Each structure stands twice: as structure tokens, then as C-alpha cells.
Image: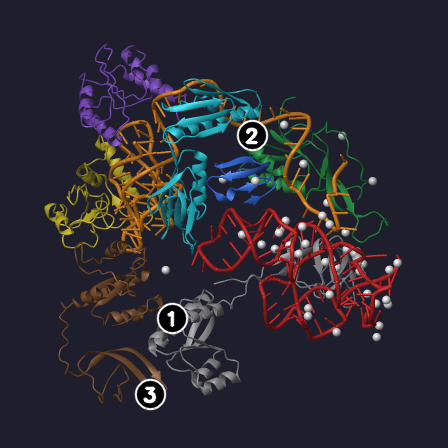
Chain colours: A cyan, B yellow, C brown, E purple, F blue, G green, H orange, I red
Amino acid sequence: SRVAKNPVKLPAGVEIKLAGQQLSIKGAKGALELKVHPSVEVIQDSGELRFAARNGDQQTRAMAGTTRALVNNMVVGVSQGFERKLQLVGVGYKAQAKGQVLSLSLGFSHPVDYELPAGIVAETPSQTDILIKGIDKQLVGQVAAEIRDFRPPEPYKGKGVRYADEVVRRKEAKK
Amino acid sequence: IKLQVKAGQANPSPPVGPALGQHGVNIMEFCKAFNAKTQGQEPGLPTPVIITVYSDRSFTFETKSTPAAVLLKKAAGITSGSARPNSQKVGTVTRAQLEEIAKTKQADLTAADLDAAVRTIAGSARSMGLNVEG
Amino acid sequence: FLDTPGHAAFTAMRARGAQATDIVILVVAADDGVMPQTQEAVQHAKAAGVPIVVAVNKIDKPEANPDNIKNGLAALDVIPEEWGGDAPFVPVSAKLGTGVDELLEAVLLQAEVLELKATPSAPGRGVVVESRLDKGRGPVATVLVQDGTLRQGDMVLVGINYGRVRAM
Amino acid sequence: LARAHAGKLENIFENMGQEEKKTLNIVLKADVRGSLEALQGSLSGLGNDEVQVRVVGGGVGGITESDANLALASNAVLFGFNVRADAGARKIVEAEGLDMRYYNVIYDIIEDVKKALTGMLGSDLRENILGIAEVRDVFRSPKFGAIAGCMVTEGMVHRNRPIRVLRDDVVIFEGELESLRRFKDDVAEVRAGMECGIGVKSYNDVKVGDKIEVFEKVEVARSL
Amino acid sequence: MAIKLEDKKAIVAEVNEAAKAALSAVVADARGVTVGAMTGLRKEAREAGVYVKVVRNTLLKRAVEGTQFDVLNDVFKGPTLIAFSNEHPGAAARIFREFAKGQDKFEIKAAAFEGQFL
Amino acid sequence: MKVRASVKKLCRNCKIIRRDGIVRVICSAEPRHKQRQG
Amino acid sequence: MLQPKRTKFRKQMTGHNRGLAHRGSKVSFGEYALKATSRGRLTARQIESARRALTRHVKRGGKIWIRVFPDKPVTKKPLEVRMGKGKGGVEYWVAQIQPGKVLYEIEGVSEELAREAFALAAAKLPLATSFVKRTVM
RNA sequence: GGAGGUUGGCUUAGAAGCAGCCACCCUUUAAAGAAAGCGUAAUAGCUCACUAGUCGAGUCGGCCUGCGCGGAAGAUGUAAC
RNA sequence: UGUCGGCUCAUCACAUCCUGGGGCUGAAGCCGGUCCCAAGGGUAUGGCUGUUCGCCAUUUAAAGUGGUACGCGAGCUGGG
Ligand SMILES: *C(=O)[C@H](CCSC)NC=O
Ligand SMILES: [Mg+2]
Ligand SMILES: [Mg+2]
Ligand SMILES: [Mg+2]
Ligand SMILES: [Mg+2]
Ligand SMILES: [Mg+2]
Ligand SMILES: [Mg+2]
Ligand SMILES: [Mg+2]
Ligand SMILES: [Mg+2]
Ligand SMILES: [Mg+2]
Ligand SMILES: [Mg+2]
Ligand SMILES: [Mg+2]
Ligand SMILES: [Mg+2]
Ligand SMILES: [Mg+2]
Ligand SMILES: [Mg+2]
Ligand SMILES: [Mg+2]
Ligand SMILES: [Mg+2]
Ligand SMILES: [Mg+2]
Ligand SMILES: [Mg+2]
Ligand SMILES: [Mg+2]
Ligand SMILES: [Mg+2]
Ligand SMILES: [Mg+2]
Ligand SMILES: [Mg+2]
Ligand SMILES: [Mg+2]
Ligand SMILES: [Mg+2]
Ligand SMILES: [Mg+2]
Ligand SMILES: [Mg+2]
Ligand SMILES: [Mg+2]
Ligand SMILES: [Mg+2]
Ligand SMILES: [Mg+2]
Ligand SMILES: [Mg+2]
Ligand SMILES: [Mg+2]
Ligand SMILES: [Mg+2]
Ligand SMILES: [Mg+2]
Ligand SMILES: [Mg+2]
Ligand SMILES: [Mg+2]
Ligand SMILES: [Mg+2]
Ligand SMILES: [Zn+2]
């Protein structure tokens, strides 16, 4: 249980609340993150944060390290931020953010308009780059995956929306 | 940029083309390199050239050692290497011929002594389909 | 004006267009870039020893970007009027009619050849552009006069056929 | 005449070197000389190593009686690109079964010539097995000399299929099955595990232990 | 890879035989400019040629067991740039100072001109 | 996706995973190495 | 395939297959062996199939022994034949296998090459097998 | 960090590690493949392999064995306690 | 306990022929091959022959494979 044993090492400006099995983290530049704990973890509080198990079961050992990682994401998510870079490849492919609506042109008859949910915000520095700014990983990653699923990449020419940290296989037509 | 000029391109610019793949600059100003450098080894040696765009258009020519492909082709036989190396000899080479260009190519080669320096060209001539003998 | 087909089965025909043109207009689409047939066309033009003026077409499309064409054509040794300056480039829109007047200005500006025709009073001399057989009036030959003047009722010798012109 | 003779000499030398080729002969008419030369040049790279296409008669203008009965004398296909046949050529085409196609784009002609070329090759005569029988005991019949009383060991045996008799793994006879019997029944098929009587008129050389093999040939053809 | 059968033993024996060289030794930590600058410092092999080498810090303590340059045990932490001279004590300290003048890497750990704790 | 009674690794980058009661092979390099069941 | 050159009698009773193989359970010639751990019988087509699948994998030296011989003839009644009317004719030859019998042996190869090659042979046999090494006692 | 001969030779408008074929050496090193992948029209430019540093105590695999998991598709209606 | 085929009328299974959803491809596109999920609805007319079947002609998105006393004569027929 290497992950569970490791303390969280929270930064300077972070407010911690602990109502037993209910936890909430307050941070500057984005706040209001909270989650509930399963009944088999003890969170001792100090200048740091550390996680321990209650039972000696297999599932308790596995879930002790999951609760540590979830809290670490919350702590970073309020102090720092989470962003996931996307880029478009192809001809005529362009994106444009107009408030809370992100319009994409991905080679269909109609242009797709995607409604960014509350919380995260997207911004387009250029016509072929999308940023998904947010404070939690699950909502940022889920939205970036929904947008990417409109026109996923092709092997023969590589066209389509792709993760900026993604490797795309390529092939050629025979002969 | 690491283009390889060929004995002069002041007037002609078929292979010079210092505008495609790099920020296009003055061609008339840059093409005068063939005059100041004046090649050095006949009007046949293709020499390496390195230029910098600098701030806006400030040209700067460095000129490196001649490539070790024309010396191994235009000085010891046919100027074209064999299609299949190490399978059909292109032309015999003596140890003195390699040592003739070894001192001229004093740039880099990371050689502490001339004993090791010859071994660098030996692997180069083998890849060309030539035959090297001591 | 001579209009030639663009497919690869008509290369000989394209050659026949090169030996009579005195100027080549190379049309290349801005989106599609340089393709095999435009390379073959510039090969024909070089073999003919003739000046080349291009017209980067379909510029009205949002894609456009008539810049990679410059590099591609420079690779085949067709220097733009900029850079060094051998042949003039010009963007046109064909079906919007933007830049067509400038293209015409560029092509008629090629008076550096001086286009001297010798006398128009010489005996006619020309080349056959095409030929066909008509069921009502026999062999019909579409010929481009090169110099001299061709008049009705004149003895003509073309290829191995000869004869005199009933009609023109 | 000189070019025709030189081409004949070269073609005869090459053909005698290789073997023979299957030709597809066409009579081609067009409206303009440029179209005719383009078609002739483009219909030369369509052949293969075993089939080829030949233009036996060209020309410019409508389809006439002369080229109609020139195609009649060469089993040729009569192609007219942007031209029409007159009344007499139409009479001739109706009288016999000559096939005449009209066109206005050269690529339709190319596609049709390719489709016609693809219909002149029918190999892949490899065999696939159906059953094997093993001979044990010998009988005689008035019409068929030697009757092999045998047992089918694998697969199936059908009354009229090509056969292959082999003893000690070497073939001796490659005819077909003529008489198949179950006692006195004249059955058409026997499955493995069943005993039967085999009779072939030309086999005539039967001995216990000889293997009899039954197969079929399926033609998957080739392509260009 | 780097096994303990002979990769640790051979490097220790070679370094021990190299510990009997000139007393002065130069140590630094090159986590900066590319190998070209490292090969630039290797150009001294033609002119000066003191040691131009860097070895594992773990095996550095095991080596130099002859009590000739024992002061380097307490200074070889993290990266090391052991550059023990052969003759003319100095040189390595002076050359690297000029090398560090024209660059931004190189930390210079200590020296070994006779018994001297940095 | 290849469905067989006997699934197993086909190269160095294959992984054996159990997902909701089914043994699967997922490859990060070659998409033909995907397998199900077994 | 494998079968006796001649036999005293053409047919045999089915019999029973009981007991363990106390005789033929040692590595007597080679260094490694394939040993049967379940009882069944090999039909002289599985023996030849497993031999070719075994010698092919080695293809460079090595000596190979076969310790099983099919000497029991079995009959089969043809299709569409009633019960009785005499015993059927001999179709193939089989060998009785009891648990603990050594089937194949090999020497002159590495342990890993023999272990790979006996795996290929065991996939052609209708019974459980195992890999063993030669010991003094 | 991930380099120099070096755009290896041929081919190609142009093939510069990375269209295709042949070969696949040397050099200073701790380490770097005539290169496994992405990208360039060809360059350029982000990776990997490999090596050095930090970390700080376990890690890898086989054998025997109890109970379980897939392999497991049918006809009037659950319908194989 | 009336045995083939035809007519009329059906009902179920899924080991799916079409339509629907997917993975791989030696998948450029248009078409394909193979495997997984899926039983809601659909799923020819004739010439020959007593034929089921089969072979032909011309269609269709497709002309599925099987169980039901090889479904169905106290529902018809009677060519075998
Ligand atoms: C003929 O009677 C045949 C012989 C089998 S082998 C003696 N049996 C059945 O048709
Ligand atoms: Mg197009
Ligand atoms: Mg699920
Ligand atoms: Mg019995
Ligand atoms: Mg006994
Ligand atoms: Mg177990
Ligand atoms: Mg089970
Ligand atoms: Mg059931
Ligand atoms: Mg049911
Ligand atoms: Mg009744
Ligand atoms: Mg009905
Ligand atoms: Mg039911
Ligand atoms: Mg199903
Ligand atoms: Mg199936
Ligand atoms: Mg289906
Ligand atoms: Mg379907
Ligand atoms: Mg599919
Ligand atoms: Mg259905
Ligand atoms: Mg249905
Ligand atoms: Mg239903
Ligand atoms: Mg249902
Ligand atoms: Mg419904
Ligand atoms: Mg009908
Ligand atoms: Mg019918
Ligand atoms: Mg009838
Ligand atoms: Mg039914
Ligand atoms: Mg039933
Ligand atoms: Mg039935
Ligand atoms: Mg019935
Ligand atoms: Mg039925
Ligand atoms: Mg009735
Ligand atoms: Mg009835
Ligand atoms: Mg009645
Ligand atoms: Mg009744
Ligand atoms: Mg009644
Ligand atoms: Mg009757
Ligand atoms: Mg009657
Ligand atoms: Zn894999």
C-alpha cells in the first residue's frame, strides 16, 4: 500500500473540513469540492493528511489507496487547476467557443454545438486547439472524452479530434 | 538551415531556393557567397553551408568541411556509388588516399590520434560499395 | 486561346499544344497544390522553351493558402515573380471573376518577345489543330494559321492530302 | 508497310520465345484523330501476361459496311466513340450477332475493355477430396471386367466423379466411376463405413490393398 | 546492463589504479548543456587530458580506498565529475573555471591538491 | 476482437485483464491482439 | 504405421484396462521423458502424429525413443449391419496405457528444448501427460 | 543527456534515422540504434532504446493443494433446487 | 395410431438471409471478408418434372436454417 501510506502534502492556502465520513476542501481560485468516505478508512488530521485502513480485508487495502488519490486530486484541483489539451487535424476542421457553447465543424452537413456544463469552461486559443479548464479531474476528463468522440482519429490520414498527448497509429493502402 | 551548395549558385537558383521551408530572404544579397568563398577545390565540389535568419534578414555564412562523399567518388573513380554495398565493389581505395583527405577534414571527427581517424572513413567507404585496403 | 484536356491519356495532345502556344498559362488549384499533371505540364512547357504564367485558382474557398504552391513550384524550378523573379504569379477565382483582369494584364504584358508575325501578305502557312470527316461536306480541317494570309480559292498542301479550299 | 513488317518480325520472335497469347480484337471508330490516337495509346496497357487487346482497324467517321464486315471477319468488337452507324452497317449488325457499343467518354471504353479482358481466363483446376475407399476381395461382371469389392474409409463416394487409383502411393489410373453398387441396388452415393462394389470399364487391374481416391475440381479462376 | 559481477569490480579496480595519479582532482556536477559541451571539455584530452570522466557516486566511495584522495568521499553526492589530473597539479580546476565562465552548467565540488578538505 | 476459448499473450505489450468476470487481452501496440473469453 | 509384422491370431477380446504401470515407468534410455498420468489407449495414428510433431521441433541432433507399441487389434462393424452374424473385421491397432507409463524419451538437447517439444507432442494425445527427468533410483 | 564522420550509397522534383532497396562501420563517452514511433512536400521539431542522478525495501517466478470462473446454442411456458 | 407431394391455416427456436448496433481487416473511397450483440417486422413469380429437391428465366433489401406424428385428409386434393 505505497500510495495509501504517502501523506498528501497540501499547499499553503487550503482549508480542511472533516465531519467524520464527510469531507470538504476549500481553496482559493476554485472551491466547493466535497466527497463522502466509505466506512473502512480513517483520516487522521494534522498539518498534513494521512490515510489508514480499519479492517485487514483485501477490498479495504485496495480502497485505502483510492481514497488517498481522490483527496490528492481535490487538493491539487483547488490550488492548481486541471486542463486537458485537444487538437483538431484535417481540412476545414475548426472550433470556436462562444461563452458556454463550443461550436465544432468536423466535416458533417450540420455544425455541432456542444454545451459546456457548469463548472468547467473551455477556451479556444486558435481554430485547432481546445483547452478544457476545470478544478476536478473526472468532469474535465469526461467532457474532453465526449468532444473527442464526435470525430475520433482515422489511421489512413490521421484526421479528427485527438488528445494532445496521444499517439495515433498510421497505415497506408496496400500497393 | 543546412543546405549543400554546389560550386556556385549566384545566378542560378534551381537548388538554392532559400525561401521554401525557411523564412524567405534576399536572394541577390545571399547568392554572392560563391564569390567570397570561391569554392576552393575546382568548380565541382559541393560544399556544406549553414545560414541564420538572425533578427529580420541578416545573413551569415559558416561553410563546413567538404562532404566525404565527393572525395570518395570524384577522387578515386566513378562519381556514383554502388547500389549494393559490401556485395559488389565500386572502386579500390588505398590507405594514403583516405589519409590524404583525413588531414583536410580536420573539423570535428573527435579523433585524438590519426590511428583512429582513418577508421571513421573506412566504415564510410564500405557503405558506398567501394573496397578499402591498407 | 488553346484549351487542352487534363487527363493522362492525352499527353501527346498536350505536346501538340506546346509547339504552338508561345505562352503557357498553368492553372493550379489553391487547395489541391501541385499534382502529377501540372508537373507534366511544366515539363512540356520547358521542352517547348516557352514562358510560363500561372493562375492559382479556387482562391474563393475558405481553405485557400496559396503559399505551399509557391514552394512546390519552386522545387520544379518555376521561380515566382517575387524572391528572384522569373515568372509572375496571380491569384484568380474563375467563377467569381476576381484577379482575372490582373491575369490578363500579366499575360499580355509578355510583349518582351515582340510577337513579330512577318508580313500578313506572305503565302499562308499554318498547322492543323484537329481534323474530322463530315457526312455532308467531306474532310474538315481545323487549322491555326501561323503566318501569311489564307484566302478562299487557294491551293493548299497539308500533310499528304493537298487540294484547294471550297470553303473556309 | 515497313513498320508493319518490322512489328510483325518482333512480335513473332517474342511470341515464339514465350508461347501464345489470347487476343481481343476490336474495330475502333472515332470522331477526331486526336481522340482516336488517345484511345489507341490508352488501350495498349490493359493486357496481361496471357491475354492482350489488339485494334485491328481504326478510322475517323461513322461506322460503315466495310468496318462492320471487317469485324465480322475477325470476331471483333465494334466500338464507336462519338459516332453512329449508318443504315447499311445497321443492317449488317442486325443480320449477324455482332455487338456494337456507343460511347462518349473514353473511360467507359476502358472499363468495358477491362471487363471483356477479365473474361478470358479460367484456371484453378485444383482438386478437393470427397472420399477414399480400400479394396478387399475381387469380383467379375459381364460388362465391367474387374469389380472391386471395397470399403469406404473416409468421406463419401459418388457415382460419377473423377477418380484416382494408387497403390504404394503411386497413381496407376485416373478415370471416373461408372458402376456403383450395394449388393444389387445401383446406388448413387456411399458414405464412409459402408461396403460397396466399384466398377470401371478401363481400370481392369484390381488387387486387394489398392487405394481408390475420389475428388472434385473447383475453378476459382484468376484475375489480371 | 550494469551487473555486480564485473561492472562494479572492473570500474573499482581501474579507479584504484587511477588514484595513484597526481594528487589534484576536480569534481563537479554536469546537469546542463548538451554532450557537445561535454565533448568540448573532452577536447582537453588532446591538450591536457586529466581524467575527463564521470562515474557512479555509489561506486566512488568504494573506489579511492588507498587513502590518497579520501576527502572526496564526503563531497561525492548526486552527480560527480571526477577529473583527477596526471601532471602539473591544477589545470583541471583552472580549465573548468574557464569552461564554466562561458557556460551555465558545472558546479565544481572540490579539489584535491594534496590533503585538503575542499 | 477475437473470441476464443484459449486466450493468451501474443507479444510483450499484451496484458491479461479480468473485466466484470471475463478474461481479456488488451494490447497497447497491435490492435489484432485483442481477445475475449477463456 | 506401427503394427506387428505377423500375429498368431487375427482378433482379440476387448478385455479391461486396470492397474498402474509399475513396469515401464522409468527413464531407461534418455534424459527426459513424456509420461502418462491417466489411463486410456493410443491408436497408432496419434503415436505417429505425435512423433512427427516432436522430431520436427528439434531438427538438430538428439536421439528419440518410442516406448509404446500398438499390438492390440480392434474390430468395427460396418454401417447398416445388424447385430450378430460374426465378429467384425480389424480396422486399426491400439496400445493399452496405464497411469505412470513412459511414452517418449529424448537426449542430446537442453531441458528447455525437450520441454517445448514434448508440449507439442502432448497436444496430439487423448490423455494427460507429464514431463520427468532421469534419476538413479 | 539522448551526439560527430553523416543528407551512408542507390533511386527520386526532392528521400536529410523514419516513400522503397542494399549495407548497418567508426569516433569522444556514462549513453545514444546508419533508429522502434509521431510529425515535414522534403527540412525543422516533440519521443523511445541506452546511460547518470534522486528515491529507500522489498521484488520476480515456479511447484503441490481446497473451493470457485470461462469453454456452455433449441424448438407450447419460467422449465437443469 | 391413414405414410409422399400440393392447397388452406399456422406456432416456436436461433446455429440471422434483409433491415438495426459494433471489433478486426492484407479496411483509401464505393463495395467486401470475418467475428460479437440482436428474433421487432419482413423474407419472389414461372418453365420442366407426381415430385420435396434440383437446374434454368426474370426479379427483390432479402428470396434464412430447423422443431411441431419428416405440423395440418372426423380441413380439401389424389399426380406418386
Ligand atoms: C458386394 O456384395 C459388396 C462387397 C463388399 S467387400 C466383399 N458388399 C455390399 O455391397
Ligand atoms: Mg480532389
Ligand atoms: Mg458493462
Ligand atoms: Mg467384451
Ligand atoms: Mg504387467
Ligand atoms: Mg489453486
Ligand atoms: Mg463450469
Ligand atoms: Mg435447454
Ligand atoms: Mg421460451
Ligand atoms: Mg386417430
Ligand atoms: Mg398458404
Ligand atoms: Mg418455446
Ligand atoms: Mg446469437
Ligand atoms: Mg458461423
Ligand atoms: Mg442475418
Ligand atoms: Mg445485420
Ligand atoms: Mg463488420
Ligand atoms: Mg429476427
Ligand atoms: Mg422472424
Ligand atoms: Mg416473434
Ligand atoms: Mg421476444
Ligand atoms: Mg419496442
Ligand atoms: Mg412460382
Ligand atoms: Mg418456384
Ligand atoms: Mg407436371
Ligand atoms: Mg416453419
Ligand atoms: Mg423435436
Ligand atoms: Mg424430424
Ligand atoms: Mg406429415
Ligand atoms: Mg415442415
Ligand atoms: Mg382430403
Ligand atoms: Mg394429404
Ligand atoms: Mg373428406
Ligand atoms: Mg381426428
Ligand atoms: Mg370433412
Ligand atoms: Mg392414381
Ligand atoms: Mg385420377
Ligand atoms: Zn500484443
Q: Is residue D117 above or below residue G45?
A: below
Q: Is residue A160 above or below residue I65?
A: above
Report in which chain the residue with disc 2 lies: G
Question: Hey, what amino acid is under mark 3?
Answer: Arg
Instruction: Please name which of the two marks, 3 or 2, marks the residue nearer to the observer.
Output: 3
Give the Cα distance between marks 1 and 3.
41 Å
For ligand 8, give the image quadrant. top right
Q: Is residue A2 left or right of residue D34?
A: right
Crowd tier of the residue under label 1, counting other residues whose Cα lies within 10 Å: few below 14, some 14–19, many 20 or above:
few
Disc number placed over residue D10 in the picture, else none = 1
Quadrant of res G128: top right
Instruction: Please name which of the two marks, 2 or 1, marks the residue nearer to the observer.
Output: 2
Question: Hey, what amino acid is under mark 2?
Answer: Glu
The residue that disc 3 covers is C137
Report in which chain the residue with disc 1 lies: D
x, y percentage for residue A42? 51, 20
Quadrant of res I6: bottom right
